Image 1: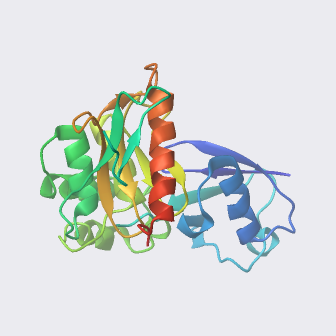
Image 2: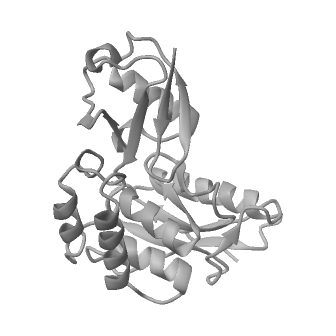
Length: 75
Length: 172
């Protein structure tokens, strides 16, 4: 299926995923498309921060759901 | 002409050189690096205030979940000189000053681009995991344009510089 991932700069990132995918897997897909290392990625859905070990299915992530990607990069 | 570890020749000719321009290693280094690249003059307080104001004025976009702390709390927190700036600050400052900001990430050997689709002009800042510096061409030029012939070569050199620095023990 398709989920979208929006950044704070307004850009949107399309992802092909299965309900079986873990948040980790998703960050790995975002790294594939965008080169962003997973350890710098924070994903947010429905006002909740998503945790590495859980699946999209755990958060009710479905068709055309939109996730928000926020990066860390603090120095 | 021998190149130092913090230098990388640009393109096949290597006539121009990309180099690290160090900024003050205080808790505001992100802001120092951006101010130098865009203004060629230091600024921290104005940049922190700009971020604080944008967050406060946009609670829907910069909600508690996005910020990882309450909106009002974040707005005060970023005003502290000890608070480290990150991607949230970069995005806001980039939008405000109409210049894209490209983060050259040493440990990842990748460039994280902010607003590359909005603004053709960009600066490069070097991130080692805990600290930011500026990248300059010929010890002066900091603002590049992605549609100028040499831009691809500049980005290639930035990535090769990042790789070399990762390999010589410079990332954290």
